[PDB]
Image (cartoon, coloured by chain):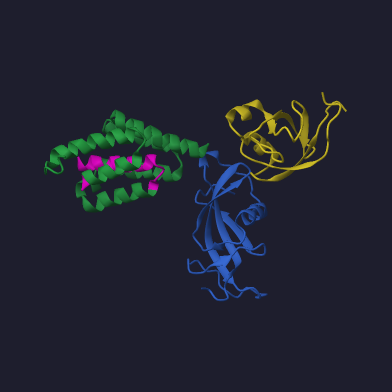
Amino acid sequence: DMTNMDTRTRHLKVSNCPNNSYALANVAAVSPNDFPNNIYIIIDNLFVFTTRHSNDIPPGTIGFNGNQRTWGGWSLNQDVQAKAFDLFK
Amino acid sequence: WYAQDQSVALSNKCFIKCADLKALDGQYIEASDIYSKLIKSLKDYFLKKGLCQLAATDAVAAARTLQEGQSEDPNFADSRESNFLKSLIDAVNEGDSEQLSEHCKEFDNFMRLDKWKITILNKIKESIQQQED
Amino acid sequence: YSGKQSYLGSIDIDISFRARGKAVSTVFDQDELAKQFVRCYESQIFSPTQYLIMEFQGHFFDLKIRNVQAIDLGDIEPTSAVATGIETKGILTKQTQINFFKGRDGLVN
């Protein structure tokens, strides 16, 4: 359910994927304190990803796999802006 | 115990077995050191020393082992084993795992790789591929 | 050590794909690489012919300083020749004239 959510922008760091299973999962691994579970979030108003609760990533940081960095023109430790998403509107 | 008894040949058999088992057991540095003792079959000892060094992501020590054998022992300098070792070091420095495989097939074609060399060479290849990934 | 020639006036770096089977032919912008290189290695002493590993766009590169030009803080016009020896040294700054060239691979364009 995506009706209510904190849509505030956050500055998050790019990092190596926590492991291969997470890369396969194709879900932005985020700490519980960051954002809810199983919800779509946009980054730079262009790149959409599905959040999933992940205790190995501290709050304030986002994990990415290689393909997503390839798509997004990003290096590691690059600081990016992340916001909530809601495709239906 | 043989080395105390001045039985060099037996002691060398013993340290060959010890070094091979150590290298297969992941103790590459210690096996390389035992191969140094064995050096101090010689061509084979040089090869194996370099190989353990390559399994320890130690390309520079492999280069020095190659140089040592080439300068100090003329039979090793011109041997197929020295050529194989230089080619492997070159591949490792290049991060080129298929080139390593190609060199392995060539050397297998002219000098059959025993099971020990195959295991260590596979470990070296895996370390290259891991750096690539 | 250097007395006055303690800053980098111009620094040339040869950039290669560490993984040359993964090579990309597109034109690379020297400035983006310059930004990230300075960001990663600001306030560090550099000498020519220095092998380094640097991440860019998911593509890892070996960066080899070709030559270092050492100047003092205050030379409006760079009068120190572009030196290639290890002896010359300088601390990386944003104002350094950074030039990038064909790596050890020769594949980068």
Residue at image location 35% in from the left, 31% down from the top: B119
Rendered colour, chain A: yellow
Q: Quadrant of the N terminus of chain B?
A: top left
Residue B84 visible within the image = no
Position of C84 with respect to A26 (left or right) is left
Q: Position of residue B59 (x, y in %)?
A: 39, 46
Q: Which sits in the foreground, C67 or B51? A: B51
Look at the image and say whether residue B45 sits in the magenta stretch.
yes
Position of C9 with respect to B35 (left or right) is right
Residue at image location 51% in from the left, 38% down from the top: B132
Q: Quadrant of residue A18?
A: top right
Count of number-bearing discs: 0
Q: Position of residue C94 (x, y in %)?
A: 67, 62
Look at the image and say whether residue C33 sits in the magenta stretch.
no
Q: Residue furthest top?
A: A1
In the image, which lettered chain appears green? B
Task: Look at the magenta stretch and give its main secondary structure.
Answer: helix
Q: Position of residue C102 (x, y in %)?
A: 55, 53
Q: Position of residue A62 (x, y in %)?
A: 69, 38
Q: Quadrant of residue B123?
A: top left
- Residue bounds of the magenta highlight: B39-59
Residue at image location 23% in from the left, 45% down from the top: B37
In the image, which lettered chain appears blue? C
Residue B116 visible within the image = yes
Q: Which sits in the foreground, A33 or A46? A: A33
Q: Which sits in the foreground, B89 or A2? A: A2
Q: Residue furthest right?
A: A89
Residue at image location 49% in from the left, 60% down from the top: C49
